[PDB]
Amino acid sequence: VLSEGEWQLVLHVWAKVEADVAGHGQDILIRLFKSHPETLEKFDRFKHLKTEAEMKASEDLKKHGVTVLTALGAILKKKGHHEAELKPLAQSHATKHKIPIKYLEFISEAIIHVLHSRHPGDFGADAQGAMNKALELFRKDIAAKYKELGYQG
Ligand code: HEM
Image (cartoon, rainbow, N blue to C red; front, top):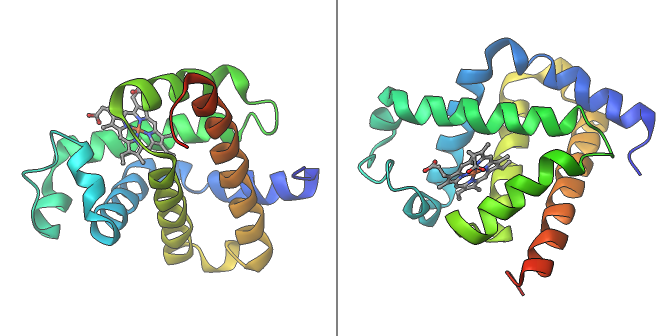
């Protein structure tokens, strides 16, 4: 499981991504596109965005980061029982956007990178391990959905 303890470490630091959802989402999506450029090819809107300055200036990119981070957060707060919210995500991601599960792993590490970037005294080894554990669960339940629809494998 995640224990009660670890969900607590998870939701404690999410509450301070909540205080600036938009600069967080923006850092994460740039960390992604930067570490893994083939991900940008999945977005039609964002493939004009060659440099990092252009990325940071795009308002459209920032709105997206808000969309992902508040869907993500809605899932984290559901802790454990997160099916209602994770199903629609899986459907669209598998059968529309064509987002391989591997990319969900890339974005997980960008999230943990970015929260290390901004949250030292709240993001220590025990919260990192909680967080990694909660991105895992998320990635595994999506993966189940994917198997079932006949994507990825
Ligand atoms: C924590 C991971 C992610 C979450 C929670 C997430 C959440 C969302 C949500 C809420 C939307 C709008 C509704 C929908 O289409 O489902 C969306 C759109 C989209 N996502 Fe994701 N997404 C995630 C990861 C990714 C990744 C890894 C990519 C690309 C590599 C991706 C590519 C897209 C695309 C291309 C769209 C369609 C709209 C647009 O053009 O941006 N998503 N996602």
